[PDB]
Amino acid sequence: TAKNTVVRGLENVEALEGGEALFECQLSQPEVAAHTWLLDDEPVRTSENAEVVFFENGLRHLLLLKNLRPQDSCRVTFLAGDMVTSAFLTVRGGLEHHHHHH
């Protein structure tokens, strides 16, 4: 509660099937009071196939995904204090259907 001002918000991301995704957001706020990150309607943590990591004490929020299936095409929303950044998710596919863990 001293200074919070986003310099760069999220941006469009393009990755082919079976690729990874990287969302780098740079904001001025070396403090953590309340931060919520919800992309698809699922908490963004889980495991290797998805998980948040960041350095510089949260000054550089980086989210890495993997094995991106066409399905992933969802919404990326990050709400950090009076600053909100949001960007689209786009990933190509191949098979029209799949019977492996729907």
Image (cartoon, rainbow, N blue to C red):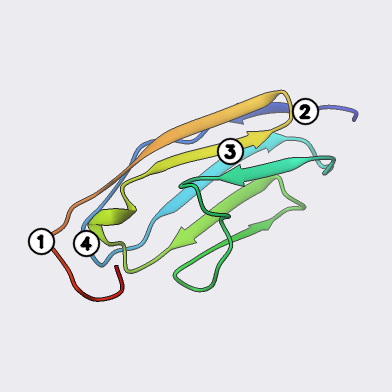
Q: Neighbour class for label 2 at 10 Å: few (<14), some, many (≥20)? A: some
Between discs 1 and 2, the one toward the N terminus = 2
Whole-number angstrom distance, CA of label 1 to CA of label 2: 42 Å
Residue beneath disc 3: 78
Q: Neighbour class for label 3 at 10 Å: few (<14), some, many (≥20)? A: many
Between discs 4 and 3, the one toward the N terminus = 4
Q: Are marks 4 and 2 in contact (CB under 8 Å)?
A: no
Q: How far from the left and from the top, in percent, is residue 100?
A: 24, 76
Q: How far from the left and from the top, in percent, is residue 18?
A: 25, 67
Above or below, 36 relative to 3? below
Q: Nearer the viewer, residue 86 or 44?
A: 44
Q: Amino acid at mark 4?
A: Glu
Residue beneath disc 1: 94
Q: How far from the left and from the top, in percent, is residue 46?
A: 55, 67
User: In the drawing, what numbered circle is on residue 79?
Assistant: none
Q: Amino acid at mark 3?
A: Phe
Residue beneath disc 2: 4
Between discs 2 and 3, the one toward the N terminus = 2
Residue beneath disc 4: 17
Camera-nearest label, 4 or 1: 1
Left or right of 26 on screen, residue 96: left
Q: How far from the left and from the top, in percent, is residue 74?
A: 36, 44
Between discs 3 and 1, the one toward the N terminus = 3
Whole-number angstrom distance, CA of label 3 to CA of label 1: 29 Å
Q: Amino acid at mark 2?
A: Asn
Q: Neighbour class for label 1 at 10 Å: few (<14), some, many (≥20)? A: few
Give the residue displayed 56% in from the left and 45% down from the top: 38
Where does the C terminus fall, quadrant-wise? bottom left
Secondary structure under tag 4 reads loop
